[PDB]
Amino acid sequence: QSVPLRNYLMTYVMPTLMQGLNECCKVRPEDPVDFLAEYLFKNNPEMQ
Amino acid sequence: QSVPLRNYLMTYVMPTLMQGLNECCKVRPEDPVDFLAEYLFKNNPEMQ
Amino acid sequence: MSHIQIPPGLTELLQGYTVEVGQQPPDLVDFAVEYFTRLREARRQESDTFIV
Amino acid sequence: KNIKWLTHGEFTPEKGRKQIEKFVSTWEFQNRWVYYADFIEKKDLIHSYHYIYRVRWSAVSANALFTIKFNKSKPADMPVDVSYIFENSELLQRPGEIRFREQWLRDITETKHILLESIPFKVV
Amino acid sequence: PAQAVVTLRYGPYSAVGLSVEHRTYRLQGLQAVLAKDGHQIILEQIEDWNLVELVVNEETVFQCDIQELEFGGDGKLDPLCEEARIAVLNAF
Amino acid sequence: LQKFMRSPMQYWNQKLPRKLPPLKESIHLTSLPLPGYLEQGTATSLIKAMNAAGNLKPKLPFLSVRRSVLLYIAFHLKAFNPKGSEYSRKKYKKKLE
Amino acid sequence: HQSTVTSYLEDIILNTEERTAEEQARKEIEKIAEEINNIAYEMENRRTYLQSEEIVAELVYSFLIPEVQKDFVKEKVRNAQRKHILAAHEIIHSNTETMLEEQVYKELQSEDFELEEEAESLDSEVPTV
Amino acid sequence: PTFDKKPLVWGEDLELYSKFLDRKEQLRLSHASYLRHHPEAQALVSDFLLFLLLRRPEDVVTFAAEHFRPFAA
């Protein structure tokens, strides 16, 4: 039963999570708020 | 002796009893009574 | 896009509304206006103190 | 005030327009802002229709939307079911309610101006 | 009309001693009644508990708590099922 | 059959009603669903637990109350098991004594 | 603006009504429990063996079936939790880069739930962080 | 020898705490469904909140009361 929900997790992660992870790896800031603002700034163009 | 019977049973026995019952049901044994009695003999030596 | 930020205060007003909604009022439109009238004294003061 | 409404078959779309316009004419207090109404599509529903009109004002502009239901499965003599919306508002107001505030028209147009001041010029 | 096309909406409920879930059996009686009257009915699992609603034209008028109904059979002796039949007839 | 042969006129003509046809299917705990076999086993189990705890209000030295009571109850369950191997049941009974 | 407000308002409503129901239930149950304790103490004087036998037989019998149903429900609740735990595990792979990891984990906890709910949830991260 | 009628918190009795949780969820979903029948309750608040955040007056209570009192019968 974990396998179906694993597949669901993957099916979200591919369109969704992986972009957020890729940006999080891009920014690598020393200040978390920098990552908050970067995340928002990338997210909105993607959600658009 | 302080504890009236309902509460005495509830607190002391029932959680452990409920858990063992759940596991016996997951067994679906030929005899619940034998399995549960043995299960308790094994657990309670550790389980308080 | 012009973004937004979350101050407090509004949250407490919504909380009061939901709590009186917890009564499950009928009469909703006026019941809500009356609820804000009740706020006008009582819940506004309470909220002002509640924040800490 | 409000006007009073035809029946499902006594209604015609043009009668609907006239009735809605007259309802808006019963609005009064800021009615130095004058209304005119626009015609909007029929929506076709399994045993029902909706049919639609917009209203617009000029004196920035105010606007209103009116909704009318039609009963494919119940008598032509069924009184029409009518509801109306302001472009800002979620509120499915109904003609029998306590009347709107024209003040909301002032409020809406002011808010439009305020967003005009707000504009993020992310302009093409 | 006769042989209406219909949807039924049904809310999850706790049987005696038992979890709150979507369940059908009294509803299966209602379904049988409606089908025998002639109709096509589709079933919808509403989140709101225990509740029964009846829909045509998208228009909806019914309310019941599933446990109020008779269980299984043609339900002929259950007054509420006849009330549903009446309401359906009136919907026409 | 002997009585029938002796006096068949008493019996041979019949019009039974439709009722009580039911042929038995012997139901099994494995065959049952979870609440049914649970109910069957638990009814005896709880009867035994109820008597054992309520009457004794048990404790044994050095043990926790919980330990004493649970262990005693499990033994009591074994000792009264409707189908426990009976010499073993009496062995547990002796331990319980 | 409307979409943002809707999300904010609905969420806050859900949370507050949840708390309100919780408090109402807490009050009611606490009362009922006090009544139960009173009855129990009185009957500890009053009781006769036959009475106790019936009373607790009722209690155990009526409880155990709900206990089984509640357990199986929590089995499926735990299955949902395991979904969230594996979502955390998936992000934990990306966490192995480790650089933001410490503060990120807090947001991740919410993100597991919100991604499990819907594909649009990432908007919800922006305010929730 | 010492004697007490120990007061029990519901958390102490699994049966009571379960009943509490079940009742809690039942109420929670009841209230949700009640608002779901009366979306207008949410809709009014939502509209007020929207125009408030458009304007962002710091006295939320003034602006909302200014919307509500015109509704007042």
Image: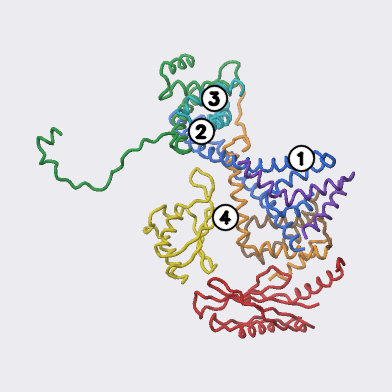
Chain colours: A purple, B cyan, C brown, D red, E yellow, F green, G blue, H orange
Residue type, numbered disc 3: Tyr
Q: Are marks 3 and 1 on the same chain?
A: no
Q: Is residue G48 visible?
A: no
Residue type, numbered disc 4: Asp
Seen from the viewer's position, the closer of residues F77 and B9 is: F77
Residue C24: percent from the left, percent from the top?
Answer: 62, 58
On residue E48, the disc is 4
Report, in whole angstroms, how far the alpha carbon at label 3 lies from the one at label 1: 39 Å
Q: Which residue is mark 2?
A: B25
Pinpoint the chain carrying mark 1: G
On residue G93, the disc is 1
Q: Are marks 4 and 1 on the same chain?
A: no
Residue G51: percent from the left, percent from the top?
Answer: 45, 32
From what the image shows, is residue H45 above or below residue A20? below
Report, in whole angstroms, how far the alpha carbon at label 4 lies from the one at label 3: 41 Å
CB-based contact (under 8 Å), mark 2 and mark 3: no
Seen from the viewer's position, the closer of residues C8 and E4 is: E4
Residue E23: percent from the left, percent from the top?
Answer: 50, 51
Q: Which residue is mark 3?
A: B39
Of the image marks 2 and 3, the number of the one nearer the N terminus: 2
Foreground tag (3 vs 1): 1
Residue G20: percent from the left, percent from the top?
Answer: 66, 50
Residue type, numbered disc 2: Cys
